Image 1 (cartoon, rainbow, N blue to C red):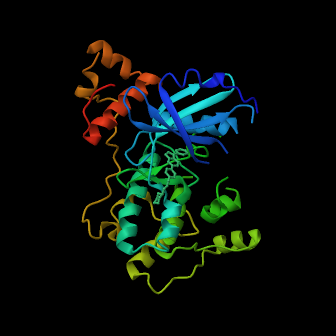
Image 2 (tube, rainbow, N blue to C red):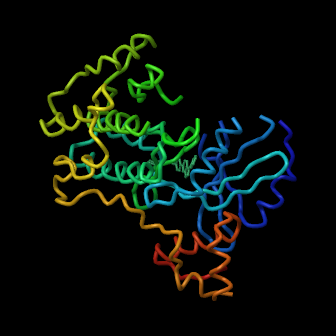
Image 3 (cartoon, helix red, strand yellow):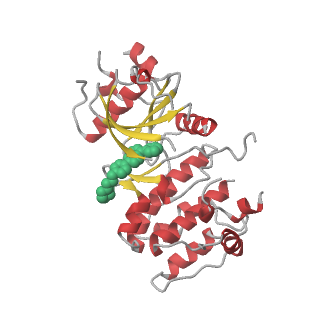
Length: 315
Ligand SMILES: c1cc(-c2cnn3cc(-c4ccc(OCCN5CCCCC5)cc4)cnc23)ccn1
C-alpha cells in the first residue's frame, strides 16, 4: 500500500512493462529489452506471505526443467520483489479442461506424460511440489506444460496447505514424495472425466471421501485408465505406485512405447556457444555463477531465442 513508482526504476532499465495477465501477488506481461523476448514478471509488495515466495525463489534457482516455468531474473527493492519468469501464452490447464469439458485418453496421455516428467525431475532433486493442481500448470507457445507456483514446495528428507481436493489422505491425517503421486492421480481423473473424484459442499464430507478412497468410475474410462487410477489413488502411501513404476507404466507406455523422459534438457553446466559468442573464458565464467541477475536472464532468454530458431542477437 505504498504505491511508490521508484521501485520500477531498476526494472524498467531491462524490461518494458505491459498489461496485467494473472493473479495474491500481481503478474504483468513484459518484454526483455536486450533480447526482445516476452516474459512474465510476478510483483510482490512487501507491505501488502513473504516466506512463501522466498521458498519458491530458492527452489526455482535449483530447479531447471523443460516442463517447469523457468526463473530468469530476481529483483528486489525496498518495497517490492520482482520475479521474471517464462511466459506461457496458452494459459492454465484448468481453463483448458473446462473449455474441452473432458479430454480423451490419448489427449490426456500427451498432457499427463509432461506432468510426470516435471514431477519426477522435482522429486529427483529432493523436492516435493505439494500443490499439484491444474491451476498450477500452464501451456506455453508450443502448447507444452509448465509447472508453476513452488511456494508450498519442500524437502521431505530435509529440515522441518494446498487444495483439499488434491490433498493426499496422509496430509489430512496430519502425518511427502508419495503425496504428489496422489495429486497427479487426481489430475489424471479430472483430465479424463472433467470433474473431481472427491468433491462435496461440506468440508468434513470432502475430507472423509478422500480418506475412504472411493470414487465413481465413469463408463467412458478404459480398463487401462481404471487400473492406473487405482494404483495412483491408493489411500495407503506405501501401497501407492512409485515414481519409478509410473515412468514406464503400461498406460503411460501406450502409443509411445518408451518411458517418460524426465531428465532435464536444461543444464547448469553446459553453456551454448552461439549465445556466449557476443560482446570467452571470462564471459562463460560470469554465466556459470547463476546469480539470477540481468546476465542470467539475458543468457537464458538468448538461449530461448536460439531454441525458437530466431537469430542469436541483441537489439
Ligand atoms: C508464475 C508464472 C506465471 C505465468 C507465466 N506466464 N503466464 C501466463 C499467464 C497467462 C497467459 C495468457 C493468458 O491468456 C489466455 C488466453 N486463452 C488461452 C487459451 C485459449 C483461449 C485464449 C492467460 C494467462 C498466466 N500466468 C503466467 C504466473 C504466476 N506464477
